Length: 9
Length: 303
Image (cartoon, rainbow over all chains, first blue to last red; front, side, top):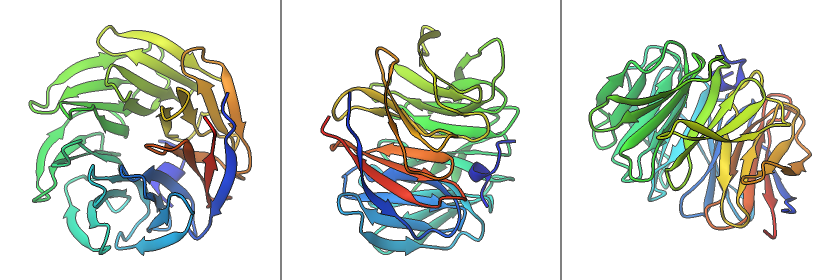
């Protein structure tokens, strides 16, 4: 994945 | 009211699309993805142009240089990469963040790149050399967005820590902090095209138009769903003056900027619309969605 496509923090 | 209608669906990424940006010259759409690739598409015919690769983890953001010749990308591999668009070659690897790089942008003169990272810093990089010129201790949580104003003298940054900050590019000093008495995490921020305003998304399903000098909230846009992801929002200026944003209910929302009324919702994506972009001269919107969808859609309006 990538950080933006994962739930933010 | 506008009448955006679907024109193309652009398939080919194998994981969630994270970001789409039109080239300043209007010819191209660039898209970044969790699949580690950047893809270049024709803005007017939707035709796939090329794939640019080299990041060894997913990419959360991509941005064009003002002359449309370069791209910069931000990756979970903790680096940014500067790409020559025509050749597809990696011209520089920007190293120094200690966690995922989340967001990036050139300044208008395109001699600088600004990046924000999960490491809670904002970095300012020299494009020619790839050197990091400044590390700003910007925030106490991941930085969700970074953006230059129209002359590049100001940077605006946002963070999960709930703050919007305005920085003097040359000195690196924080000129202004916006707070909301509540801390919703701030998931996106950018200057208005004129630089007088800032558009800020917060993870309470709310977009706000701010006068950063005055420190006043001018406008609030609601009705969409935004609680989990950092969704891009935009000023649409080629026809009617709209606010455009993705939404976690898989729709594209378009509001009248002045009245705050919803004027259109674009249906067809099958996952969170993480990203929208507005074409620089035509009434064209690009939208892109997450893992259940993986496609980019191009929409066209008469106004």
